[PDB]
Image (tube, rainbow, N blue to C red; front, side, top):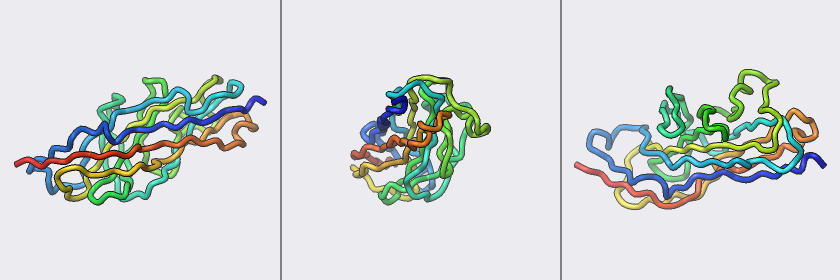
Amino acid sequence: GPDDYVPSQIAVNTSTLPGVVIGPADAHTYPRVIGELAGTSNQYVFNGGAIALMRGKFTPALPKIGSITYTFHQGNSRDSSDFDIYDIGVSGLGIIIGMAGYWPATPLVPINSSGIYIDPVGANTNPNTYNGATASFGARLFVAFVATGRLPNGYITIPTRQLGTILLEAKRTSLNNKGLTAPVMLNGGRIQVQSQT
């Protein structure tokens, strides 16, 4: 009865990307980060059962197409990270992903492998580490767009894509055994691009 946790997705929205202004000095330089979506948060990525020691593991779902170093502006990272660049099905574009715990002081964890703990980050260096026993597991999501080649002017349609999942791991075996996941989404929309001289 204690393991009545349910997942809730976390998403970012294409419509929050600023218009992409491409200056002459950049137009032919790739890969390059071309803007950030607005960061989002969800207190309740997993919630509902008896309080538990929990942690969340991110599994990417998109094809890797390269890597790049970057420092996100949002989330207050001091130092860069190396990110996998992921295919979204649009020529000239890719995305990079960072995630963090719900608590705002927790650090951005770059997505650059098949699996990482997004919170607590100490689980990446200690297999016995979980968050302290509590009702909920939350997260923050950060996505940026990457130009991997030349882009046309005007509107560019971006499909909705499942970026990956967060897996609920727990110290309690009966909860861990459920293997609950929550989707991590990019909601589609249209970006705009304009070169300038």
